[PDB]
Image (cartoon, helix red, strand yellow):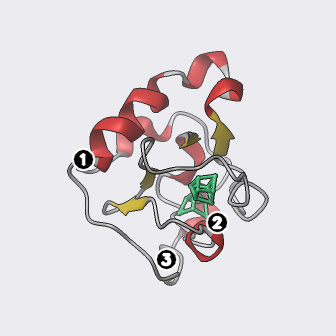
Amino acid sequence: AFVVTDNCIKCKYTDCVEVCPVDCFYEGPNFLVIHPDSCIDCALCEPECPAQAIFSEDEVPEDMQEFIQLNAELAEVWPNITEKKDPLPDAEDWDGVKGKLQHLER
Ligand code: SF4
Ligand code: F3S
């Protein structure tokens, strides 16, 4: 499974959903997650993220390990997203800010 990590929060570009063959992204107010069961590990999404927030599960940085289980839990509750949409308004002010997990909205 590929995992979306911290830098997606408050950026939410949605470029990643274009390339997914299996539509495994689920949408929250200010973040996206990948559903782990459904992901086929094709890796096509991680070159597409402008925030460079997507990682193969086995490459998630040590300080972002929480995101692996988070993608798994939130994917069970959030709606499926299959079309790109516009980035959140202030997306590049927040792109690159560390520690955005305190800002995640359910
Ligand atoms: S690795 Fe492929 S199947 Fe998994 S979320 Fe990314 S684009 Fe979809
Ligand atoms: S910022 Fe997030 S919405 Fe997709 S394109 Fe990157 S993982």
* Residue wearing tag 1: 76
Q: Where does residue 44 sit, x and y in percent of width and height?
A: 73, 60
Disc sitting over residue 89 in the figure: 3
Q: Looking at the rendering, in which quadrant would you find the N terminus?
A: top right
* Residue wearing tag 2: 92
Residue at x-position 73% and y-position 65%: 48
Q: Where does residue 19 sit, x and y in percent of width and height?
A: 66, 72
> Dividing the picture into quarters, in which one does residue 63 lie?
top right
**Mark 3 secondary-structure assignment:** loop
With 76 as the anchor, is 11 left or right in this view? right
**Quadrant of the image where one finds ligand 1:** bottom right
- Distance from disc 1 to disc 2, alpha carbons, whole Å, reads 28 Å
Residue at x-position 39% and y-position 28%: 69
- Distance from disc 3 to disc 2, alpha carbons, whole Å, reads 8 Å
Q: Where does residue 18 sit, x and y in percent of width and height?
A: 61, 77
Mark 3 C-beta to ligand 2 under 8 Å: no
